[PDB]
Amino acid sequence: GNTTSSVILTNYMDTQYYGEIGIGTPPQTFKVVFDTGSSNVWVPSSKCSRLYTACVYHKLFDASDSSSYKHNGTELTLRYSTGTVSGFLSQDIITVGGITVTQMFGEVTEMPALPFMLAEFDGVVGMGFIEQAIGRVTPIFDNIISQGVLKEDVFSFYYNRDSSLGGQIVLGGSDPQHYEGNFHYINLIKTGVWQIQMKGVSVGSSTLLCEDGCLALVDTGASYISGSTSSIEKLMEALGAKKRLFDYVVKCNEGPTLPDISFHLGGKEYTLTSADYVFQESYSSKKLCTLAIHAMDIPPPTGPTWALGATFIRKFYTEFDRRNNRIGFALAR
Amino acid sequence: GNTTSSVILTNYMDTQYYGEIGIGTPPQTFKVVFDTGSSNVWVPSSKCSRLYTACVYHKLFDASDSSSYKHNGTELTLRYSTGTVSGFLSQDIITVGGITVTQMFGEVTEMPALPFMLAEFDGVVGMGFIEQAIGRVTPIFDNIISQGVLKEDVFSFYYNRDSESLGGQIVLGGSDPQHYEGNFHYINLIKTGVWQIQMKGVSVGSSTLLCEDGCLALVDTGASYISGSTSSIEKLMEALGAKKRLFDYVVKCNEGPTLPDISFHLGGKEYTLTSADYVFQESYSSKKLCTLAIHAMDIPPPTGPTWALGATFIRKFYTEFDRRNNRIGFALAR
Ligand SMILES: CC(C)C[C@H](O)[C@H](O)[C@H](CC1CCCCC1)NC(=O)[C@H](CC1CC1)C[C@H](O)[C@@H](O)Cc1ccccc1
Ligand SMILES: CC(C)C[C@H](O)[C@H](O)[C@H](CC1CCCCC1)NC(=O)[C@H](CC1CC1)C[C@H](O)[C@@H](O)Cc1ccccc1
Ligand SMILES: *[C@@H]1O[C@H](CO)[C@@H](O)[C@H](O)[C@H]1NC(C)=O
Ligand SMILES: *[C@@H]1O[C@H](CO)[C@@H](O)[C@H](O)[C@H]1NC(C)=O
């Protein structure tokens, strides 16, 4: 086709990026995170029990208000790293940017306040592949492509830094106003996960980590750049970061002193400077600053793997190419 | 005709959108707000006393340096919701977006420091109907239509989000598809003479708690905010738990991200704003106040009482002002 659809995102604290979708006729509007690490669509239910606060605190779909809903009941449990959610299939019209599409989505009838009570958004739009879809339900993007319509079989993510639009997704292309120069692509290790091969992680001038290769999931639904507990321990130790109770911290004044961290992908070096990975809330010698890199031991089959989340995307605008099973990166602007 | 002209705009702090016009021979350049809520053109005059500080800080039209000027001199006063300007009429050639028109405009000689010292712009280009023109002067758009150059008898507005980007864009005689998506949905004007439509109701969250029974919505490009009657606002705000200040309402910064959506029921479609769209989020602190870009303004009859949908709304929905067919169309902005 010859269209593109974009969704303006809200950037909450550099940790949550979400946009609007409407579900049903007329549409009921929800805030969703668009997640490449998963493939299901889900929102909180009409029918959610109001005990778990999450539902009491989220917008709930009311199928009784949809002129276009179509009953489905097949039950679902959606398991992510942070948590799990349960509900059941439903069939309705979803508006995304300027596109309307019929979609099987999950009606979230069980939704735990950990982490759900921390979510500034209502639900999730999985931008992952069918192979990861609970219920082997056709993922929204796939459904949108069926539609002809989009110019290219691709979708792009822009995440801004918290200070402006908070971010933007473009379905069917990329927006040149938000990147510099040209994309360089890295091919997926295999169809089914948005995961590529990584040939090294350098601290400053030196390959400290992943010397003999590793995996990197490009995850729009993850806040930080993460690696296993061991990798991160090693990385932090190279940075001189210490763990302050819950997290790794640095003296805020010495943040501008930390080395660059480079990620070797597709034969290039994707470099983040300390300003790109240190939360410089402050610059005092009297305060401790947090880092936007965390350990995350991801289970196989997917893991162990590094996850390149918002911290990475902020630096590199990203294009997910379905057609060619590759990811394109360009300097965000 | 087959022409379409666009005016690039500057976005100052999400509250003032303006562009440039040239008046006179040679051209004397001014920043102006293009206002659908009024129909006169005006800029500050070189005849404005310097005892008016706003005239000391603004670009001044000097008829004596213009060889195309035509004297008129009739007096006029222009009353806006937030201030008033006074002066006299002149005639000159004005260029706007590459279009040149001979236009009667006001040379302002009295320009209050409050609010004008706070304007980044110099003057105003009213985009309304002659029905609203002070001094019966013909509005710019009518003069431009008279030329037979525009592809269509419509003008469209794009207002961007601020930036750290194009601040905005006005298209004369069309729309720019680069700036909207999906389709336009239209509401016929209650009447010609005013860019005001019927509004079916107002929801805070889901609860149509406002405008049950109908109300009016003035689609105002010269308005920074979305506004309703003081009583409307007191109720709206009640629901948001925002505190009333002198000129605005506030919420505790931390509360901001969690405010409910606000819907506007117009012609058929619901126009939904999220808190991110109407709160000025400038921190997430517990001990800091965050303004809302929804205000109370009681506009007098005959136009009011009405809600005014200004920049808060337009940022999210691209707007087309259809003269030919007396209607306004909205589309999702991009
Ligand atoms: C292969 C898997 C690692 C993919 C992973 O499940 C999906 O990307 C999943 C999608 C999120 C979307 C927001 C709601 C919770 C699920 N991300 C993840 O769980 C991320 C960590 C995975 C190691 C990478 C956690 C996310 O950063 C999570 O904190 C976002 C959140 C914020 C506030 C409340 C709840 C959740
Ligand atoms: C029928 C009326 C409601 C129409 C209304 O007077 C016009 O739209 C008028 C046009 C402006 C143009 C800039 C110079 C001041 C007048 N907008 C208004 O006054 C608006 C409130 C009306 C309830 C809608 C607020 C305006 O946006 C005002 O904040 C802009 C301003 C900023 C800084 C300094 C001076 C002015
Ligand atoms: C619900 O959808 C699932 C998966 O598409 C399907 O296999 C099941 O038959 C559906 N139920 C109904 C009401 O047909
Ligand atoms: C001023 O302009 C009005 C409108 O054209 C005109 O009718 C009036 O005669 C003019 N007055 C003078 C003194 O030029």
Image: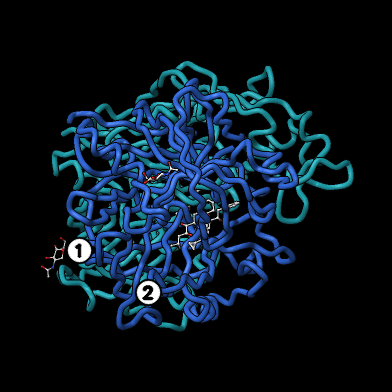
Chain colours: A cyan, B blue
Q: Is residue A269 above or below residue B207?
A: above
Q: Is residue B116 above or below residue B179?
A: below
Q: Quadrant of residue A86?
A: bottom left
Residues at marks 2 and 1 touching, judged by CB atoms closer than 8 Å: no
Q: What chain does mark 1 sit on?
A: A
Q: Which one is closest to the eye, mark 2 or mark 1?
A: 2
The amino acid pointed to by label 2 is: Val
The answer as to whether the residues below labels 2 and 1 share one chain is no
Horizontal arrangement in the rendering, residue A17 relative to residue A208 (left or right): left
Q: Position of residue B94 (x, y in %)?
A: 42, 31
Residue B5 appearing in the image: yes
Left or right side of B94 for B150:
left
Query: What residue sits right under mark 2 in the picture?
Result: B202
Q: Is residue A215 visible?
A: no
Q: Classify A77 as above or below B1.
A: below
Residue shown at 43%/64% (left/top)?
B308
